[PDB]
Image (spheres, coloured by chain):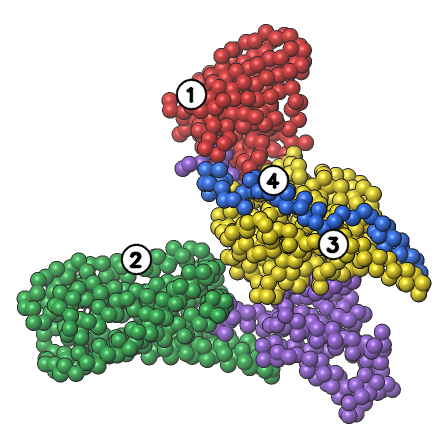
């Protein structure tokens, strides 16, 4: 029981180890670019006038 | 005649001393109760008592200045015609709502056999206004019928500022108010005695928690009954002699002055009831205490 | 599944009273509003009365106000219409119509078979340009209608209903709120409108949707129906 | 045994070394050149009243108007958020519900809890009443989260340290996701619904493949139980709220924690977390009865949503980002805009 | 007023739903909620009989409807779902008296630890506990040969059923850190006792009266 669980954990760790990882700087840049691109369409970020606000 | 020591020195200073605390307590209670949910009739009655107490504290300084002597005769006649009437309306609204709280607690704890009435319901909210306007209906004429011009500016008497119909209607409304208070007092005494009897037969004791619960409930009920009695019973046993004194001219000047002083002291006690209420009534309210702790701290 | 069966029709002398009943099955009758709708032998549909779920609100048409009384017994799932002092103009087939109301609901979606009863001004008027349209299967047919007042509301909903009544059958809901296809209706039917003028377009038409098409308004409450556009051939 | 443990330790060390090598910079040191979002002032517009117990879950509809909520009084209420009208009220067989899901099509709703059963109710029944259409059973722990993928499949997380993708028509677990050593407390579905992240009580989140069925990635860093999880709108990142006072943002492609949102004045746990439409604002519900809106790029506390008298249990953002729903233990839902 | 007919009917439907919800809440508020807890085979099954996840037992006694919730078999982190039972009227905790001579860690010590955790947690500060010391008939036979010193070495009393039972009850009651605000209703049951329901009724009646006093602003 313990041996099988340990082998499964080792296999899972090996599978997760060989994945391709990008630099944190590139991921952060992509995240910031998405935020900048979609900021103009975010009602929470920029308050919407009462004309286009369905909760007024 | 007059001694100028009670009605102008002791009464104004005692009213100021009670007012400087009552206005603050009522203001903070009203500020806190704005966020308190009205999920039960008890909370609605507490909010109504808060409103009545706030108006009573607001109308205290008008009297204080009227009987202090510094204010003009116009202020005195305004107090006689408006401020005093509002003060009495608030007092009797508070008394009726104390009776309503006693009945609600009796219904919730004792579980009476006449539970089909269902007074403790949403309709109690309507009952609340049905309370308020009722005393308004008992005091609205007392403001408009005080139209008689003052014969002299040296002194003004409320009886001399009312017409014959107005004087008769006030002599009847003051009696109606006293009768209503006595009915409410008898109901409150009966309901609280029943609640105490239910509590005594509730727990089997022999436990620290049981003893603490019994002691706390008994102390709260005793405090409520004692404060109600002390603040109101002397006033409502002295009001009828005083209104008879100022509606009948055969009671002589000395007894009239003594009754006036007694009425003023008893009304001062009924005024100090506004300060005594928040410690005894509002403080024990669990949502009120929780919101007070959350906000003040 | 859902079934509405009417009873109580027949011959009534003028000035008499008759009690129409509508037994409901296959659905939660208590949670639905119920309408009574008339159809004269050749004059088309006409709304009569309505009772809300729980009998909260009860309404009648001006023609039957003061004479007809609509009620409902939820425990027995029955809809009742008591008619007193029946006139000669009341001779018509009566339908009990199931109609529920919530956001996104499809009211007027089921109609009962109906029973025939034979007796010996400011509301929105719905008009239909064409009464009979000769059509051929496989083509596209556009049925048009107009309203005195715009059916578009401040909430963005345009309360127009397109019903189809086949020969020998009760009216069937096709479109609700001028754009929504009713459940069980094929994608052939499409609703469109500009607020006051509306069209219903049918593509690849077959012989299974031949009948009279009715337009009903639901913006102003006194529900009025169009004259009815009959499809032939 | 010992050799396998040593190999697992070596693999973990290799994973940590790869993560450290890929961590050339930080999101905080990159987003210093962008302006802050300022003080976000979301005022409450709608207050949904009618739940009489603590509200445990709430999910928005894809129309951004219909909103389902679950309360401990055994009630599942579907609200018209625009008019505060109660569209539906579903009595639940088990009143101990901790999760509820609204189908993307809107034809179905889901709930579940201590009964270890995910109940799926049909909202578009011909009879006109909401009836239970399915009762997915097989989880041996309490249902903590559930999320529809379509009208026929749903991913549900349980307290038995496993997740399950079900087939509603058949009622059987299509796929079982195992590997969490603690109770799974939350789920989040990717925009493409091909992957999903589940946070558990082992202070770990796991990125799972829905179709393939194996744990694609594992993310650590939280010091206590992870109670909430939410994908970033881009789908390449997700935020986790834990029993500690920290939210943490992880990147799928970087396989690393990006930023930590925390404050010294905050010491209570985190129950719910969600992103705005653009993902710039991260809304997190806390045990201190308040909600905090953080700048997801700068970790600055942009604003506070206060007005709930008890613990904020559930939080959601509409698909159009128009408003934020917060359901608290005080038995009220508040919509903020 | 500024509403369509369909909007008005939807508002009417919402009002009907509100009325139904208020009626359901009023009906549920009068129900007595009990949370059944125990260290294991402590007699919880017998208590449920005589009175895959959550188990609900509904029974009416003396015009009081009791819902008893058994959380046995959950086998998960209790802290993640115990807060769901914050508002229960009472907690019925069952402890096997004969477990003092058994081990899993001694069974009685584990039961005491679980009782301490349940009583002193942040969610049951004021919730009352009905302690059912079950299997007293077997405990009487066991105490005749097996001394109580196996579980509690500090027990200086004579190895008698009454003295040992009193010592165990006192030890269990000593685990309450909030004795002023919380009451523990210890009861002794052996098998198929009809007085257990009466004891539960009395305890929940006291709890209900205390709750009514607290709600009315009188305590
Ligand atoms: O100058 C003073 O020293 C004071 O004397 C008066 O004393 P009194 O004339 O006895 O007034 P009350 O009879 O106690 O009542 C005052 C007003 O309220 C009305 N009232 C009295 C009693 C009552 O139960 N309800 C009620 O509306 C009266 O008709 C009267 O107009 C009042 O207390 C003050 O208005 C006045 O300022």
According to the image, label 1 marks what residue?
C148
Q: In this orientation, does residue C15 appear?
A: yes
According to the image, label 3 marks what residue?
D23
Mark 1 vs mark 2, CA separation in Å: 49 Å
Say which residue appears at 66% left-offset and 10% top-offset: C137
**Mark 1 lies within 8 Å of ligand 1 (Cβ measured):** no
**Mark 4 lies within 8 Å of ligand 1 (Cβ measured):** no
Residue D141's quadrant in the figure? bottom right
| Place of residue A56 in the rendered image (x, y in percent of width and height, measured from the top left) | 46, 43
Q: Are marks 1 and 3 in contact (CB under 8 Å)?
A: no
Do badges 4 and 3 share one subunit? no
Q: Chain of mark 4?
A: A
According to the image, label 2 marks what residue?
B133
Mark 1 vs mark 4, CA separation in Å: 47 Å
Toward the left, the furthest residue is B151
Chain letter, colour blue:
A
Frontmost of labels 4 and 2 is: 4
Q: Nearer the viewer, residue B221 or D323?
A: D323
| Place of residue D203 in the rendered image (x, y in percent of width and height, measured from the top left) | 74, 60
Tell me the shade of chain D.
Answer: yellow
Q: Are marks 4 and 2 in contact (CB under 8 Å)?
A: no
Q: Secondary structure at mark 1?
A: loop
Mark 4 vs mark 2, CA separation in Å: 61 Å
Tell me the shade of chain E.
Answer: purple
Q: Nearer the viewer, residue B145 or D43?
A: D43
Q: Nearer the viewer, residue B207 or C197?
A: C197
Q: Secondary structure at mark 3?
A: loop
Frontmost of labels 1 and 2 is: 1
Decide: few, some or many residues near mark 4? Use Cα within 10 Å; few <14, some 14-19, many ≥20. Answer: few
Q: Which mark is residue A37?
A: 4
Chain letter, colour green:
B
Chain letter, colour red:
C
């Amino acid at each position: 029981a313990s041996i099988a669980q340990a082998r499964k954990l080792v296999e899972q760790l090996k599978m997760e180890a060989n994945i391709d990882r990008i630099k944190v700087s590139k991921a952060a840049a992509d995240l910031m670019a998405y935020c900048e691109a979609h900021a103009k369409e975010d009602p929470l970020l920029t308050p919407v006038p009462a004309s286009e606000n369905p909760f007024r | 005649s007059q001694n100028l020591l009670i009605t102008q020195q002791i009464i104004p200073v005692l009213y100021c001393m009670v007012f400087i605390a009552g206005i603050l307590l009522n203001g903070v209670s009203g500020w806190i109760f704005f966020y308190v949910p009205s999920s039960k009739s008890f909370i609605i009655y507490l909010k109504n008592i808060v409103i009545a107490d706030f108006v009573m504290s607001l109308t205290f300084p008008f009297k204080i200045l009227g009987d202090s002597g510094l204010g003009p005769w116009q202020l005195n006649v305004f107090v006689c015609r408006v401020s005093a009437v509002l003060f009495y309306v608030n007092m009797y609204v508070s008394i009726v709502f104390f009776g309503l709280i006693s009945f609600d607690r009796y219904y919730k704890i004792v579980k009476p056999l006449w539970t089909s009435f269902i007074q403790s319901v949403s309709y109690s909210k309507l009952l609340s206004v049905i309370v308020w306007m009722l005393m308004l209906l008992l005091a609205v004429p007392n403001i408009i019928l005080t139209n008689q011009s003052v014969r002299e500016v040296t002194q003004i008497k409320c009886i001399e500022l009312k017409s014959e119909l107005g004087r008769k209607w006030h002599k009847a409304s003051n009696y109606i108010f006293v009768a209503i208070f006595w009915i409410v007092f008898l109901l409150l005494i009966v309901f609280y005695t029943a609640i105490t009897k239910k509590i005594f037969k509730s727990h089997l004791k022999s436990s620290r928690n049981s003893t603490s619960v019994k002691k706390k409930s008994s102390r709260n009920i005793f405090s409520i009954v004692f404060v109600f009695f002390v603040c109101f019973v002397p006033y409502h046993i002295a009001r009828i002699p005083y209104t008879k004194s100022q509606t009948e001219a055969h009671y002589s000047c000395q007894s009239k002055e003594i009754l006036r002083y007694m009425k003023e002291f008893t009304l001062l006690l009924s005024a100090a009831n506004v300060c005594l209420d928040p410690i005894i009534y509002f403080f024990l309210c669990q949502p009120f205490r929780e919101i007070l702790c959350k906000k003040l701290h | 599944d859902v079934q509405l069966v009417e009873s109580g029709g027949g011959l009534v002398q003028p000035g008499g009273s008759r009690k129409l009943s509508c037994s409901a099955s296959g659905f939660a009758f208590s949670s639905f509003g119920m309408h009574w709708v008339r159809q004269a032998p050749e004059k088309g549909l006409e709304w009569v009365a309505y009772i809300s779920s729980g009998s909260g609100t009860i309404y009648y048409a001006d023609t039957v106000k003061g004479r007809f009384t609509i009620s409902r017994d939820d425990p027995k799932n029955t809809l009742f219409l008591q008619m007193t002092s029946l006139r000669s103009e009341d001779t018509a087939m009566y339908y009990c119509v199931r109609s529920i109301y919530y956001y996104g609901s499809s009211p007027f979606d089921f109609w009962g078979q109906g029973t025939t009863l034979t007796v010996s001004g400011s509301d929105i008027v719905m008009t239909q340009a064409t009464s009979s349209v000769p059509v051929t299967p496989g083509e596209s047919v556009s049925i048009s209608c107009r309203s005195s007042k715009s059916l578009l509301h401040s909430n963005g909903n345009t309360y127009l209903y397109w019903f189809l009544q086949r020969p020998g059958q009760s009216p069937q809901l096709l479109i609700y709120r001028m754009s929504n296809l009713a459940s069980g209706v094929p994608d052939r039917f499409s609703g469109s409108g500009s607020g006051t003028a509306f069209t219903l377009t049918i593509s690849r038409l077959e012989a299974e949707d031949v009948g009279v098409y009715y337009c009903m308004q639901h913006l102003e409450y006194p529900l009025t129906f169009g004259a009815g556009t009959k499809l032939e051939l | 045994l010992d050799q396998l443990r040593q190999e697992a330790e070596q693999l973990k060390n290799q994973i940590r070394d790869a993560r450290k090598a890929c961590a050339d910079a930080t999101l905080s040191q990159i987003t210093n050149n962008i302006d802050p979002v300022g003080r976000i002032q979301m005022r409450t517009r709608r207050t949904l009243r009618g739940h009489l117990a603590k509200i445990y879950a709430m999910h928005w509809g894809t129309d951004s108007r219909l909103l389902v909520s679950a309360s401990q009084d055994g009630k599942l209420i579907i609200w018209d958020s625009y008019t505060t009208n109660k569209v539906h009220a579903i009595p639940l067989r088990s009143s101990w519900v901790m999760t509820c899901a609204y189908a993307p099509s809107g034809n179905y709703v889901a709930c579940g809890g201590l009964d270890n059963i995910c109940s799926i109710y049909n909202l578009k029944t011909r009879e006109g009443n909401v009836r239970v259409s399915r009762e997915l059973a097989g989880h041996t722990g309490y249902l903590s989260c559930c999320r529809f993928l379509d009208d026929n499949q749903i991913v549900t997380s349980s307290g038995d340290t496993t997740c399950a993708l079900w087939d509603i028509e058949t009622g059987q677990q299509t796929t079982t996701f195992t590997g969490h050593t603690g109770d799974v407390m939350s789920l989040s579905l990717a925009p493409d619904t091909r992957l999903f992240v589940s946070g558990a009580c082992d202070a770990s989140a796991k990125l799972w493949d829905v179709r393939e069925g194996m744990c694609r990635q594992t993310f650590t860093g939280h010091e206590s139980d992870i109670n909430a999880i939410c994908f970033f709108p881009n789908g390449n990142a997700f935020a986790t709220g834990s029993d500690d006072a920290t939210c943490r943002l992880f990147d799928l492609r970087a396989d690393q924690e990006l930023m930590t949102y925390s404050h010294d004045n905050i010491i209570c746990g985190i129950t719910s977390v969600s992103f705005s439409k653009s993902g710039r604002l991260l809304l997190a519900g806390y045990d201190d009865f308040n909600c905090n809106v953080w700048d997801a790029l700068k970790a600055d506390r942009a604003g506070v949503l206060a007005g709930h008298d008890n613990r904020v249990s559930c939080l959601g953002v509409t698909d159009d980002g128009m408003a934020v729903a917060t359901g608290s233990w005080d038995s009220f839902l508040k919509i903020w805009n | 007023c500024t509403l369509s007919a369909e909007d008005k009917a939807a508002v009417e439907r919402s009002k009907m739903i509100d009325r139904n919800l208020r009626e359901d809440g009023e009906k549920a508020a009068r129900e007595v909620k009990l949370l059944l807890l125990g260290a294991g085979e402590s007699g919880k099954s017998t208590i449920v009989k005589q009175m895959t996840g959550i188990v609900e037992t509904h029974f009416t006694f003396k015009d009081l409807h009791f819902k008893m919730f058994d959380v046995g078999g959950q086998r998960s982190e209790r802290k993640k779902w115990i807060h769901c039972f914050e508002g229960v009227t009472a907690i019925i905790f069952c402890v096997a008296l004969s477990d003092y001579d058994l081990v899993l860690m001694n069974r009685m010590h584990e039961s005491m630890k679980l009782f301490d955790s349940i009583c002193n947690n942040k969610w049951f500060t004021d919730t009352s506990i009905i302690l059912f010391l079950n299997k007293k008939d077997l405990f009487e036979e066991k105490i005749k040969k097996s001394p109580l010193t196996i579980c509690y070495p500090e027990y200086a009393g004579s190895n008698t059923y009454e003295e040992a039972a009193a010592y165990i009850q006192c030890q269990f009651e000593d685990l309450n850190k909030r004795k002023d605000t919380k009451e523990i209703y210890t009861h002794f049951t052996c098998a198929t006792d009809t007085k257990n329901v009466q004891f539960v009724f009395d305890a929940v009646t006291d709890v209900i009266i205390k709750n009514n006093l607290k709600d009315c602003g009188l305590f």
